[PDB]
Amino acid sequence: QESSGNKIHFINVQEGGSDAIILESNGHFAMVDTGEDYDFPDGSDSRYPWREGIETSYKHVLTDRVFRRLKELSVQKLDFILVTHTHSDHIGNVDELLSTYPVDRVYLKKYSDSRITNSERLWDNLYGYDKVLQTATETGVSVIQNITQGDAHFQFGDMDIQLYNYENETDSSGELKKIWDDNSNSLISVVKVNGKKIYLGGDLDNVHGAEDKYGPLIGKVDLMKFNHHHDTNKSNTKDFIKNLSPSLIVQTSDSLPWKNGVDSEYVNWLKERGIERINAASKDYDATVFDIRKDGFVNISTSYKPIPSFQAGWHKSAYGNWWYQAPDSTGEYAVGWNEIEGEWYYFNQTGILLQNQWKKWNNHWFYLTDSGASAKNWKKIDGIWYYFNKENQMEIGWVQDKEQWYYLDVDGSMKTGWLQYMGQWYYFAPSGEMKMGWVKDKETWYYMDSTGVMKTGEIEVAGQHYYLEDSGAMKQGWHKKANDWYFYKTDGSRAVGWIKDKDKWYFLKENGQLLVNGKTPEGYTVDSSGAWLVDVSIEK
Ligand SMILES: C[N+](C)(C)CCOP(=O)(O)O
Ligand SMILES: [Ca+2]
Ligand SMILES: [Ca+2]
Ligand SMILES: [Zn+2]
Ligand SMILES: [Zn+2]
């Protein structure tokens, strides 16, 4: 007849892989996935702990591109948002979209962290999933989580849409069947219009037999979105592509088909088949766009406005805060940790630079200085010395720096004075360094060995002898070792020959032992205490 047109916009990545797809049909708009969003959980909420691999790079955020395309299309409302799975690069902008546009319904299969067998593949799935459910209820939007056969087949404008892999698969106890990764759970969408079929399968893989199962059921299509961006290890199996036999494959990725490197053999196998393969990646246009005509798909991408220019660098908001647009971005702003000209800066999820504050991140403490730059090496904060390692983490415990040892307390604060560490005693200077050798604390001397350990008992250093008491304190004056008396001088050193103590003269032998009841080398007499009997005449 005469509708206003049928189009599909695959939002272009800057790099990496992410799915956001706009369906346009006779003035109706809907989305299949929504791309990566700026937002992410920082670990401050125990429900959504920080996990290695959660996306924080502006290079992977599709938010600007999604909302620019919708605005450029004069979208007033979305008939539906379909979410294929809970990965941030698919579900990311759903809540932002629900906050921005009226939405009639969201398709969202059940998820829980428990149904994923691998701890290492949880990331921020639940955070993204909860955002959809929470924001949908807050904006009045029905979430279809229990898709019936009836639900699975519906009209959208001129488009006929059929879903596959839509059921929640459960065990005897009604809890979700376990899978290796949420990719296996991908909600499949097949779109029919103007005699053309388009397959849209999110990150579908064959680990739990999904490609084996749905290949034969889906059958011949024209345009196939590649499953899972670029992967050929577990997705896009030969049987699946033979079953669908597309003339055109669109990858939502800047990468070639990939399996530990370019999968050149798979690339060639696709060519031998006459399949056209296109990457939805661009620095210049928000989307790879096809006009879906009876006589074929027309690439109309460049018929839209190019991405606007931007001024790179640091920018100051109206409220005095800082945000940043990297010169290698296409306008997307920095969030989370970002290395900028040799310093590390942390930006919150809305893109604001944090300054002059402690920040806990992935179980370590960081201090963001005046400029925002994370502290490195010694830093004095609120009157206390702290030490930050080469990775900006506040150190605790023993730290070696510039050929000296330091100890940082449990709260990061530098230790000075006495420390009992692992059953032994150490002493740190007021400037923090662990002291070796002779150290004066208050009005007592102590002797620490080469490793800083306070010594006890008799010692010899540089030809002189000292006695350290059990507490470590250097002895001064009289000391009995076994059956002999010794005298330690003011400097601690063991005396030899004649010494004067308390107006009496005492003779210490070669070996430091006190002569008692006998004659000195010159023939003087000493009493039982070793004191010289002054009245007794010299006698040789
Ligand atoms: C969630 N994630 C983006 C960190 C992992 C990658 O997800 P996927 O697109 O490879 O399935
Ligand atoms: Ca995100
Ligand atoms: Ca979001
Ligand atoms: Zn993905
Ligand atoms: Zn995925």
Image: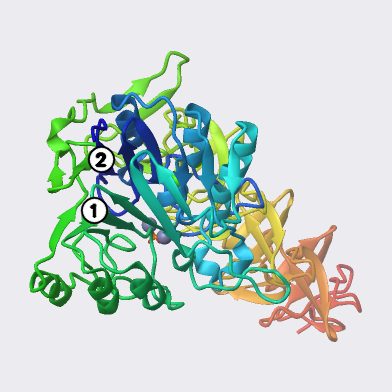
Residue 178 figure quarter = bottom right
Identify the image quadrant of the C terminus.
Answer: bottom right
Number of residues whose C-alpha sits closer than 10 Å to that of mark 1, classed few (under 14), some (14–19) or many (20 or more): some
**Is residue 11 rendered to the left or right of residue 48?**
left
Left or right placement of residue 346 versus residue 57 in this view: right
Name the one closer to the observer, 323 or 416: 323
Say above or below: 18 vs 166.
above
Q: Is mark 2 within 8 Å of ligand 4?
A: no
Give ligand 1's quarter of the image.
bottom left
Q: Which amino acid, by three-letter code, is at mark 1?
A: Lys
Asked where in the image residue 29 lies, by quadrant, the reply is top left
Q: CA distance from mark 1 to mark 2?
A: 12 Å
Q: Which residue is denoted by mark 1 in the rendering?
A: 196
Question: Is residue 306 found left or right of 77 in the rendered image?
Answer: left
Quarter of the image with the N terminus is: top left
Name the residue located 26 percent from the left edge and 68 percent from the top edge: 244
Q: Which residue is mark 2?
A: 7
Helix, strand or loop at label 2? It is strand
| Residue at (57, 58) in percent of width and height | 148
Residue 36 position in % (x across, y down): 40, 45
Q: Is mark 1 within 8 Å of ligand 4?
A: no
Image coords of residue 137 (percent x, y): 64, 37
As drawn, the residue found furthest toward the front would be 1
Mark 1 or 2, closer to the camera: 1
Task: Tell me: residue 219, above or below residue 368.
Answer: below
The amino acid at mark 2 is Lys
Coordinates of residue 447 in the picture (x, y in percent): 64, 65
Give the camera-side residue of 442 and 171: 171
